[PDB]
Image (cartoon, coloured by chain):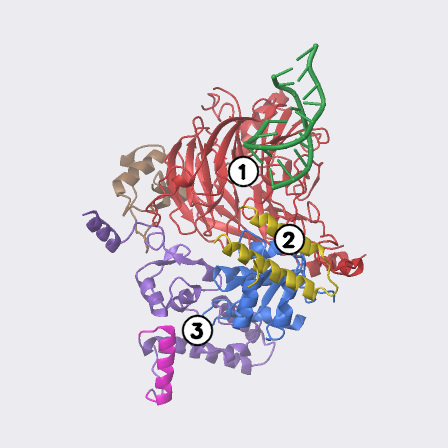
Amino acid sequence: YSTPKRPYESSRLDAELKLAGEFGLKNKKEIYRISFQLSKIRRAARDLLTRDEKDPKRLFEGNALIRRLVRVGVLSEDKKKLDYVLALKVEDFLERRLQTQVYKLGLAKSVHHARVLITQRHIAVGKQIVNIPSFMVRLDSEKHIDFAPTSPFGGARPGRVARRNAARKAE
Amino acid sequence: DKDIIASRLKEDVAEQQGRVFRYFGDKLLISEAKQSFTRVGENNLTCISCFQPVLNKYTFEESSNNKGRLFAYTVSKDLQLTKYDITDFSKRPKKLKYAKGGAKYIPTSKHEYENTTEGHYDEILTVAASPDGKYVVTGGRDRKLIVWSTESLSPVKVIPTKDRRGEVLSLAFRKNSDQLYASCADFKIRTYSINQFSQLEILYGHHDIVEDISALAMERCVTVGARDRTAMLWKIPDETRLTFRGGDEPQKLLRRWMKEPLFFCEGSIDVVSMVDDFHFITGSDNGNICLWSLAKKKPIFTERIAHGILPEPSFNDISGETDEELRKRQLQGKKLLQPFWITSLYAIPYSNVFISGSWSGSLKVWKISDNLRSFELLGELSGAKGVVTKIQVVESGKHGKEKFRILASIAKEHRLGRWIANVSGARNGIYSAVIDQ
Amino acid sequence: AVTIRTRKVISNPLLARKQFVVDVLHPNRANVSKDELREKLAEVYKAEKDAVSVFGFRTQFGGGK
Amino acid sequence: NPKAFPLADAALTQQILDVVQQAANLRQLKKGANEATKTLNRGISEFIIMAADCEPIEILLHLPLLCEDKNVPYVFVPSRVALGRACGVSRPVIAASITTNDASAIKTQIYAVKDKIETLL
Amino acid sequence: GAEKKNKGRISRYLANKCSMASRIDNYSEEPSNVFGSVLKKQVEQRLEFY
RNA sequence: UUGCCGUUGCAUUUUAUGGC
């Protein structure tokens, strides 16, 4: 978390409203968390730009930074230079979280249904059941998301309501 | 003497060492096999799983239950598995027993895990007969898998995959055991114990439809998924994997040629077998045959377009013009030639030899070099006019003298889709080659 | 049906004792019942349920292993 | 320049076929010639793919006259059965079209493929 | 008026067959008849279920 | 040998081809 400088601007209020609305968020603190890590990631990216080209500090840590950001997927591999990290912005960071990513993957039909069936422990990334929205699925594990093995949307037993109503229809 | 000491080592200690030992590359004449075709009219046969009883299973007490005859099991696309006797070499595989699946094997719950109905919905894909000869598992696009008895073919148990899209695409037994690695097209590999009739562990981490699997004595699995150009080698008892990618691009192949000739990129890995616990071979969608080890990522030796290139269409059915010059130009030279992408491949375990099959009408036999970094032709087996769904090799003879029976299931369309390009006279049947010495 | 595997099997004749990290995979059971799993571990080893001893367990998140 | 002109080479063929496969698994792909021209004049078509070995070629060659009118890019590939396997369907398709969707997870790959084929033409 | 259940699905079959035939003999610059003949054989083998 | 269709060949089997 990190609080803004002047938080009560109507421009920032409409900003938080739009981002929370079309990405399905729960308050402004999620926006502030990933905006703080975006701010520290490009504040660490700009001083490497201000120092000299082929300074091995710049070379190694810039290739380190863009190797991390390609693997998270906020930086496409066609733009493998450090000033594109400066050009990066926060909707690319909350595009990669698990809630929005599963809604783009289908199987959820709305962003808030994506959030709520994540929180019902229904969705596992490959092997591990994950019950948090803010997850930042990496580019390799993008295509590993399906329903959990121990979930009625997966292949497990039908749930509580299903077998209760099946018993009352047996009555 | 020393020869009897060597034969006692090559009894089992070589195969528990797990390196390629059973060298019969140059020892094996090829060009005079008894290459008998057998027609079976059951609508695109899709699998072959032979079963030979191994004598004295690592202690004594010769085999498991007849006493000592071989078998084969096979699978249609219109829901019929058939049990063939193969034990009489230089004789046709005789049909023995039959089991079909109709529409009445559709359940009525239809929306849960329970596919308890014993037969099949539709489109049975592949079998595997257990090396202790009690059961044969079967599995297809109906998200089940069945244990059939090896005598009366009675549904011992039905194992559902418990999935919306878990079509079972290839099964494999770990040899001299009854652990079963099924390769389900929801990107996963399942493990089953047949004697416990249960599911040990499900193992994820692939990236597309895991369409072929292979296994050997130790707890390895080598699977390939299709549209990710990769090959996963699973080691279970430490629970990890190894990702061997392709990486042969045509511009760099042009750099390797331009010192002094068409080739194209890689669609998809299709088929696997593993020649030991330390090397395996795959067959891709550009006809490429890769020989791969444990230690490296790139191919050790990738043979090029293996079964040749498909014939281009004629003048008569490319454009519908009248003039032969324009219908010549509509062929675009050689630019739209596409390879014979291979459809089945099998290596005899710990052997100097393997075999590959597609719809070129002919099996191709290959021999690995002695230093285990190259391989080459051995011959050509032309009586299998049609698509090769699965090849399995059964053997007989002495400790040094061998008598082989190659069994290649032949259909007239591919075992997953339909995808023909004018397949010319393909009888649904079994190619069966006796080859000796 | 569960499957118990072991890993990093290092011997230790300083206590005449063979130590390891055990991992059980139970796909649908709750837990693996320390006594029952230690007697199955003694069965897959040489002998003596009373002389095998497993002590450091935890079930990982989401269940299964 | 025979009739099916922008025919992709091997590497671009393979990357457009893998983006076809993930589009089909995401249910963003409409397949076949007449469903292709239906989504073309609906207006939701990002780019279209045509197999240039069909029997004969004109059955899909009707599609360039609509697509270059409505300003969407169009590629030919060398094989119907390759396109069928890449669509994830049993019969050989010859035409395929990616519906535009902003709720896609494949959007950047779609755009990179589009830039490569537009520089191809 | 033209294109002369059991008539409905064969009307649809004839419709997309003749649309395909139209594509052939339009975009072919100097058309042939052989594809029209094989389309005729296809649609007559199709309606020969009755 | 095969669900159908065309076959070598018996002193009935036999036998490997090509159409759905």
Same chain shared by disc 2 and disc 1: no
Subunit under mark 3: A
In the rendered image, residue A151, in percent from the top left (x then y), is placed at 33, 54
What is the chief secondary structure element of the magenta stretch? helix
Please name the amino acid that badge 2 sits on: Lys
Q: Please tell me the colour of chain B.
A: red
Task: List the single residue furthest toward the left.
Answer: A171
What residue type is disc 1 on?
Cys
Task: Decide if residue A84 is on the left or right side of residue B202.
Answer: right
Colour that chain D carries in the picture? blue
Q: Classify mark 1: residues with Cα within 10 Å, few (<14), some (14-19) or many (20+).
A: many
Could you tell me which secondary element the residue under label 1 belongs to? strand
Mark whose residue sits in front, 2 or 1? 2
* Residue underneath mark 2: E40
Magenta segment:
A8-26
Check the image and report above or below for A2 versus B366. Answer: below
Q: Say which amino acid is labelled 3.
A: Phe
As drawn, the label of residue A93 is: 3
- Residue D82 lies, in percent from the top left, at 61, 55
The CA span between labels 2 and 3 is 59 Å
Report helix, strand or loop for mark 2. Answer: helix
Q: Which residue is mark 1?
A: B47
For the colour green, the matching chain is F
Q: Position of residue A35 (x, y in %)?
A: 40, 78
Colour for chain C in the figure: brown
> Which one of the lettered chains is coloured yellow?
E
Q: At which x and y percent is residue A26?
A: 31, 74
In front: B189, or A154?
A154
